[PDB]
Amino acid sequence: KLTIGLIGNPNSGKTTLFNQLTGSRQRVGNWAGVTVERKEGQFSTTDHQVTLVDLPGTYSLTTISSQTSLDEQIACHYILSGDADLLINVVDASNLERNLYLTLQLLELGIPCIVALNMLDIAEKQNIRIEIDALSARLGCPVIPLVSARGRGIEALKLAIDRYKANENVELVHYAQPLLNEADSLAKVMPSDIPLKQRRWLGLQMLEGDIYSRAYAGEASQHLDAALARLRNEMDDPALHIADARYQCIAAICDVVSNTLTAEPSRF
């Protein structure tokens, strides 16, 4: 038996993939404490009986700008609740750079994950070519091309689920040493139920100015002002650096991964 969480952007073809996997074997209700719909369904692999949980559409698990989205909170809450044994991240190939911000957050949290590259046919109309193994090597998790024809992308996805394992601990984003040391101090006073790696993540998001992470912080929210001011002795703007270090990482990956599909040559 298994429980998998389906996660991705609003326009990533996530809902369509859910229906194709589960089919008629579905159940409907709502998330705890709200009227927002919660779909669940089941399908079988060679070994496992999978229980697919459809999460709401989301671009990011965090937010700044004082803008709240209940769909994002519900998504982030389920991820941190550790209910699912595995996650399937639906990624749009025609908007890779934008979609990878969510993908990165799932990998930083240490959640076992399988990326499903969707809308490859639309990417080819944009003159875009995706390097699959180059992407997989940098993310440290398997990347399955979700081929529509004959539902053979679903078969490859089921094959990946039976082989699933802990993600390869690669170097994703390269933050500054003071930010990591300060985020670790916030992790000490955070509640001990949450894993160490996830506590360090939460504390890093608090420094950038996240509002969702403060719900799981506890007494660490009181130490934030002292910790944030302490970082400004070394760095000019901590919040700016975290955004740049994150952008730099994704920009580096997209340079290698996203290539031009076809072009008429002008030289020999």
Image (cartoon, rainbow, N blue to C red):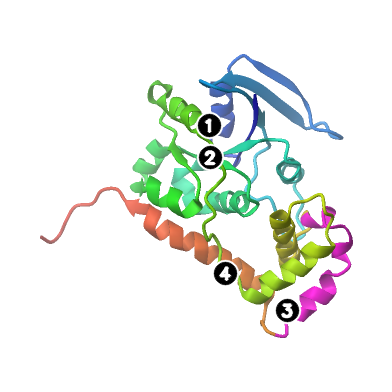
According to the picture, the residue beneath numbered tag 3 turns out to be 231
User: In percent of the image, x 82 and y 31: which residue is there?
Assistant: 35
Residue 1, located in which quarter of the rendered image? top right
Quadrant location of the C terminus?
A: bottom left
* Secondary element type, mark 4: helix
| Mark in the foreground, 3 or 1 | 1
Horizontal relation, residue 237 to residue 114: left or right: right
| Mark in the foreground, 4 or 3 | 3
Dot 2 amino acid type: Ile
Q: Which mark is residue 161?
A: 1
The mark that comes first in sequence, 4 or 2, is 2
Dot 4 amino acid type: Asp
Rounded to the nearest whole Å, what is the CA distance between mark 4 and mark 3? 16 Å
Q: Is residue 226 magenta?
A: yes
The mark that comes first in sequence, 4 or 3, is 3
Rounded to the nearest whole Å, what is the CA distance between mark 4 and mark 2? 26 Å
Q: Which mark is residue 114?
A: 2
Q: Is residue 104 above or below residue 177?
A: above
User: In percent of the image, x 57 and y 34: which residue is there?
Assistant: 14
| Mark in the foreground, 2 or 1 | 1
Rounded to the nearest whole Å, what is the CA distance between mark 3 and mark 2? 35 Å
Q: Is residue 25 above or below residue 96?
A: above
The mark that comes first in sequence, 3 or 2, is 2
Dot 3 amino acid type: Leu
Rounded to the nearest whole Å, what is the CA distance between mark 3 and mark 1? 42 Å
Horizontal relation, residue 15 to residue 92: left or right: right
- In the foreground, 82 or 94: 82
Pointer 1: residues within 10 angstroms few (<14), some, or many (20+)? many
Residue placed furthest toward the left: 268
According to the picture, the residue beneath numbered tag 4 turns out to be 244
- Is the residue under label 1 in contact with that under label 2 (CB below 8 Å)? yes
Q: Point out the stretch of residues depicted in magenta.
A: 213-233
